[PDB]
Amino acid sequence: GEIQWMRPSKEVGYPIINAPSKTKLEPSAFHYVFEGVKEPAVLTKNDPRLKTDFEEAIFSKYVGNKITEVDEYMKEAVDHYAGQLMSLDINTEQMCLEDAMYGTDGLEALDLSTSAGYPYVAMGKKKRDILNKQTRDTKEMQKLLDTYGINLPLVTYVKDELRSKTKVEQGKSRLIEASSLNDSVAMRMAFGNLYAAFHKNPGVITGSAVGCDPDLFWSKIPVLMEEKLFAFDYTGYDASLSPAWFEALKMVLEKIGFGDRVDYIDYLNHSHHLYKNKTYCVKGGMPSGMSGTSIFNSMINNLIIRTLLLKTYKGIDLDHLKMIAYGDDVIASYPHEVDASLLAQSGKDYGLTMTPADKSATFETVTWENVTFLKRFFRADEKYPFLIHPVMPMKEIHESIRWTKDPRNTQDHVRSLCLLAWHNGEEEYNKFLAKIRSVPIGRALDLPEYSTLYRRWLDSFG
RNA sequence: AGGUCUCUCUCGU
């Protein structure tokens, strides 16, 4: 991924965009009960905590594109992957515009709580002004496609979120690309039938976890897996993906019956952006807040591991490779240890820089005791070893509870952390309840017990 | 101040 030019919006007649500057994250009643090192990521150049140039920092994510031509390894990775997807027999029909707006089985309606992008936002128009849920009115939307068309500019925003102190002072805040309401809809009409089929089939065929409830799905996973596992960590995966890879994605899309719409992958590969008072073009890298980012990133991720395996294990039967990906994240098995230490080399050529799983320095071997996926570990139930707990570690939960974006939801926030916390087990969980109850506000909360949550778990495999 | 998924809470037939 690499920028190409950048200039003052008014140079090109583009408006200034209001990008807010005050984090909504304020410390909570519980800020001092628990311990945590994480702080609200940086939003402007005049930040006390800053240690370098902001603008420089944030756009650094674009390191450049390496490969640009589907090599002979990639081309075969396409075939196998596309082959699997074919087993699913995916409806290739364009999605009904009414469906692509307000949703259908397997695909949720557009989000009315979020911005419509450019140009709707420069006039101050809101998704809620074009869309009505009861009527499910298509008309006015349809005029806006005739009007502004597709392939519109993405509005870039800084994410408002807690990050590590280094990341805060070092300036490595994350970046959102806000989809025009125009393209979300057009993307959907095309790939809506693709999106759902995925949403309906998390697993090792699709190779995507998009759509799985971890509380139930953590137990089905070890079954759908080979013996020796492997895993690693990407650096900047998104803003580092290279034009070749899209051509690879388009190829899989051709091979499964989506040949016409492959146009839209170019508008993701080659995109243009309004950051405040700047404008700029970018060759490569997924745009994050565009439609299908979960499903495309995932699909590409399926191609990479498939590829990089081949470059190393010439003569490896990919027909026994079992992976599930969630964008960059991934958990994967082959009956023999596919030494990840190497893969990360074959990577840095393809623009991909892979580090060892979970900030370890060394490429540790992977096991069902140290493997994470969607930030949760695997622990069999003490009473039913065929039942696996997804374990978010207390540390992360601590970090969440120290802040809030509105004390109104204090109750909901905390209830919500217990539903994650209690898989660590009765002792740790009851310890967590007492720390909450250590302050007056905590003692206000209606929280569930271990026995109720555990009951509920078992019940739901029923 | 984006795209999604899961869970949960609140109110409705």
Image (cartoon, coloured by chain):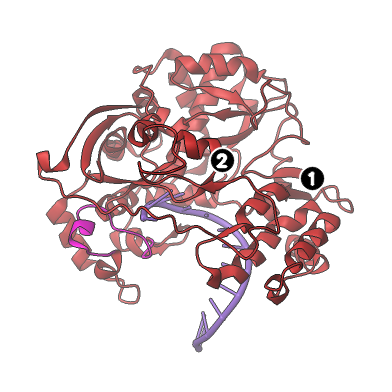
Residue that lies at the very extreme toward the right in this rendered image: A383
- Magenta segment: does it hold A189? no
- Image point 67% across, 73% down: which residue? A441
Q: Is residue A276 visible?
A: yes
Chain letter of mark 2 equals A
Q: Which residues are magenta?
A: A111-126
- A423 or A133: nearer the viewer: A423
Q: Mark 2: which amino acid? A: Ser
Location of residue A357 in the rendering, given as x and y in whole percent from the top left corner: 64, 29
- A29 or A134: nearer the viewer: A29
Location of residue A163 in the rendering, given as x and y in whole percent from the top left corner: 53, 43
SS state under label 1: strand
Circles 1 and 2 in contact, beta carbons < 8 Å: no
Q: Mark 1: which amino acid? A: Arg
Location of residue A35 in the rendering, given as x and y in whole percent from the top left corner: 69, 51
Number of the label disc, if any, that sits on residue A379? 1
- Across the whole image, how many numbered discs are drawn on residues? 2
In the rendered image of the structure, the colour used to display chain A is red
Precedes in sequence: disc 1 or disc 2: 2
Name the side, left or right, on which A198 lies relative to A361: left
Q: Please rate how many residues cluster around mark 1, counting C-alpha atoms within 10 Å: few if below 14, some from 14 to 19, many from 20.
A: some
Q: Is residue A298 visible?
A: no
- Image point 77% across, 64% down: which residue? A433
Number of the label disc, if any, that sits on residue A113? none
Q: CA distance from mark 1 to mark 2?
A: 27 Å
Q: Nearer the viewer, mark 1 or mark 2?
A: 2
Chain letter of mark 1 equals A
SS state under label 2: loop
In the rendered image of the structure, the colour used to display chain B is purple
Location of residue B8 in the rendering, given as x and y in whole percent from the top left corner: 63, 69
